[PDB]
Amino acid sequence: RYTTAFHRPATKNAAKAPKYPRSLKANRNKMDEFSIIKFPLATETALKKIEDHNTL
RNA sequence: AAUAAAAUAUUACUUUGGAUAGUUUAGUUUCCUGGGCGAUGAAGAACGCAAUGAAUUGCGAUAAGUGAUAGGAACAAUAAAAUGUGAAUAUCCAAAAUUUGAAUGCUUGAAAGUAUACUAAGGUAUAUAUGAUAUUCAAUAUCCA
Image (tube, rainbow, N blue to C red):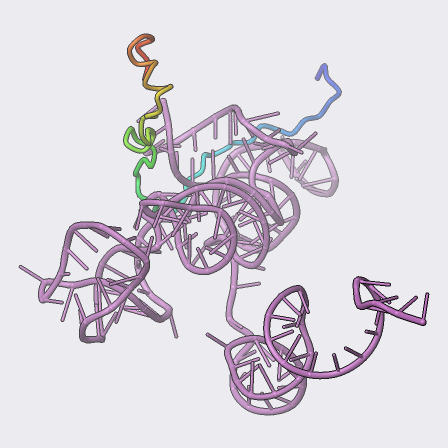
């Protein structure tokens, strides 16, 4: 057989097919654009960047 | 010999100190009833959440609280807004339940991370050992054409 090593044969490998859902959690994203940004920084240091550097 | 400054002695008032008396939402012991945790993720740990919070308490991205059921007019340190079209308050209930931790895809030091499959993100599942069933195999191990 031109080789000495014996390795485990490649038997068939079915994919997982659960009979009931593993979780009933609602499909809701808890990180949206309203929760990502809390509030703008309102310090005078942050207020100086708006006019010149065009940054918020 | 002499003076009473210091010294000494007693009482009253004051002070330093916190004894004594009165008091107790705290303990100790005995007894009665249970002894009701966890892969459906426990106990423990961390972080976060109050209009003004640092601790503590309560809670978990629905945050000092949501629904339902009882309950019936308060809360307060200050100001707000809501409220008999139901405020406080209570619960073996319902929803929701961050990161970890037996911790369980792999890694984990104070580590930031990262793979595959299913349903760009998000969410699930994938540790080790093990019982039953199904399926694909391996070994001439026993026969056997």
